[PDB]
Image (cartoon, rainbow, N blue to C red):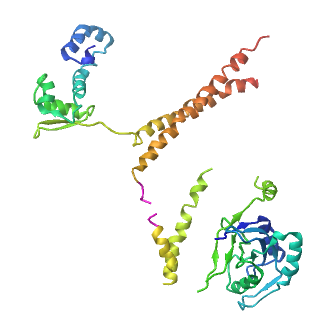
Amino acid sequence: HEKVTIAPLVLLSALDHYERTQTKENKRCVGVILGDANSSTIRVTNSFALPFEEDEKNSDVWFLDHNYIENMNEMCKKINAKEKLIGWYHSGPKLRASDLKINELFKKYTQNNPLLLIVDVKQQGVGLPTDAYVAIEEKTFLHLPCTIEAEEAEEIGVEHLLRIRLTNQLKSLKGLQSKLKDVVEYLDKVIHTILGKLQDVFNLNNLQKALTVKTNDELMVIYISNLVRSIIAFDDLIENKIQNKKIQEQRVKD
Amino acid sequence: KAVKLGDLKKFTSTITKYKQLLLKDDTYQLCVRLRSNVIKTGIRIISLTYKKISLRDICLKLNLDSEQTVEYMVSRAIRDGVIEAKINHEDGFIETTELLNIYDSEDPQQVFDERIKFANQLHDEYLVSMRYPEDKKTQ
């Protein structure tokens, strides 16, 4: 649908918020998220901690003001018009139905159904420490996948951070692990439809055909470069020391 | 010259002629074998090129040579592979195989692997000698 950009700049401060707020698992540091929400891709420019209170001792019990956003957007606007409210974040890592209520607050404040944002404040597992949701209906809410933009400005200072194949395999288990269990979970959790929804694509395997040969046929040439790959080695470094040592081992005049 | 044909007499004739020279080099022990091998070689060639030939037409080469020793002689040949064919005497049909494939198999890629395995020959050797000036130049 409108699946969305992600601003690391957000992501960072977001945890600072979590940090700043000293939010803990008891809590989720919540706040605006900013961008412009029109397109079938939405962007996250920015986001703002909404000074907030959360109580799950009573689910619906929690405290927040909008009027931040009120004054906020003003400045935000005054900062940039393109702030236009896309939605909001919280810590998370997970939902709590009161979110729904909370979600709807922003509905007043957003063009579309606004955008939830989960964060993993511990960034624990994997790609994203994050989920973004839009409500729905039998309610619906949903995660459309999202990701980063450029923000090379980001990417550059980013560059100042960090500092081939086997990984690619490694996830191999992962989904499968849960997956079968996830059945057995829901199986023996409810011992839904979506599981069968999965079930079909399963045969999408043992699918392989003598089209396999193509592979073999293909792989051949792949190797043809072999004699060439190291041929230049074969020729290159070997006849290189014979011209430097004969020069040298014999150099040896006086 | 014989082994081109492998004509046992003409074959032997050489030996008959050169045995001492063979003996001189004691290559004599050899060839005593390749005799029928080339016979079987011919048997394989410009001959197995039908999905058969008959018993007797392939026996013809043995009707040139021998009979129903053919059975042995062909089994003698088939024994080793070195040819690929079958028969049924019950058919009387000496049934001479394709030997036809493509590189669908890993057979090329075996050779590629063979080539692959060699990828270290000169490659790893370059490092084998990288030393000498490079290291002695330090001296």
Magenta-tinted stretch: A202-208
User: In terms of secondary structure, what is the magenta stretch mainly?
Assistant: loop
The image quarter containing residue B127 is top right
Whether A218 is drawn above or below A5: the answer is above
| Residue drawn at the location 43% of the way across and 49% of the way down | A212
Q: Residue A39 in the image: state x and y as whole percent.
A: 70, 69
> Toward the viewer: A205 or A123?
A205
Considering the image in quadrants, where does the N terminus of chain B appear?
top left
Quick check: is A204 in the magenta stretch? yes
The image quarter containing residue A133 is bottom right
Q: Is residue A107 left or right of residue B96?
A: right
Q: Residue A150 in the image: state x and y as whole percent.
A: 76, 58
Q: Is residue B115 left or right of residue A61?
A: left
Q: Residue B21 in the image: state x and y as whole percent.
A: 29, 8
Whether residue A31 is visible here, answered yes or no, is: yes
Q: Is residue B43 left or right of residue A18?
A: left
> Toward the viewer: A226 or A209?
A209
Whether A24 is drawn above or below B68: the answer is below
Whether residue B33 is visible here, answered yes or no, is: no
